[PDB]
Image 1 (spheres, helix red, strand yellow):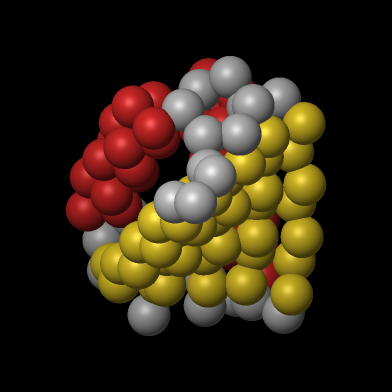
Image 2: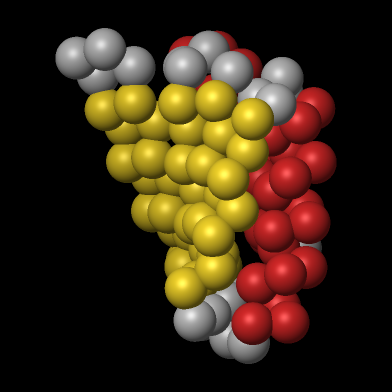
Length: 92
């Protein structure tokens, strides 16, 4: 299935959120939800990796995560694909 790994680091405080969705609908729920946790924490570095079923899927997700990070002010983003896992890491 779809594995969402959210890792927020911020001086002596590391948060690791792991979700498993199946809807792309309840994904919008996780998405929206993560957007808030991060707005609040306002961390320098934020990493999100999503293990998709196919690389073409990982791409659609990378497009999603890019807009998420951009909107939230993270503007120097690294997008890395590792098989079916996409890892978008941004810095504020």
